[PDB]
Length: 48
Length: 47
Length: 48
Length: 34
Image (cartoon, rainbow over all chains, first blue to last red; front, side, top):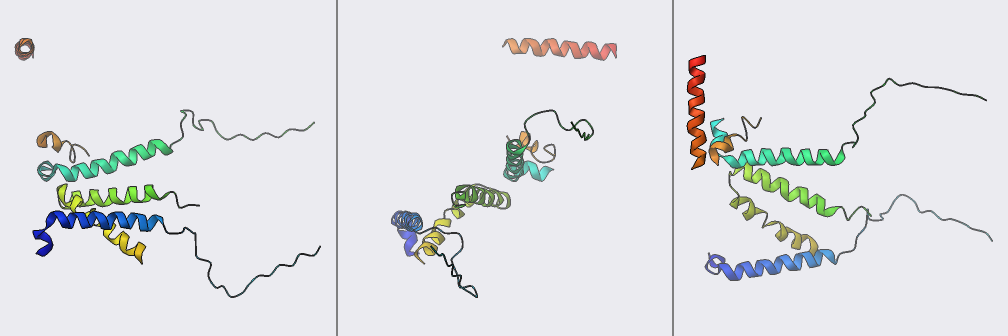
């Protein structure tokens, strides 16, 4: 009821939430799958 | 039917779905007219 | 690299939702009243 | 499909009169000939 009395201001804080959302989203790093713990680890050996 | 008359917007949704599927079809289909009209034929040559 | 194919994902997404909404509810105001709510979950996921 | 689905939107959505009269004459003559 309170947020409806102040429809305009609540639409403003909405737009603020939306803008923050898109910005917070695009600031995230990007990857395919997260490199996770498999059963093993692979070591390679190169000799001169 | 008459119910499609009274609510134009449901028909608009079915339509839009159809014209979108068609345009996407246009985008994906091979361009030229000549298909594989003739039967498959296989030759083999030597020298 | 397959991450810049996203605007077609959400393009098809909000189009499918807007249409089905305009199909069931039989108007165009209500779908706009719903697709307005999609960034509210975005800010939550991004902030998470 | 449109005839069931979209063509319902038909229902949902001077010298020209010279032609109307002339056309009306043609269908009357068509009636007579038929």
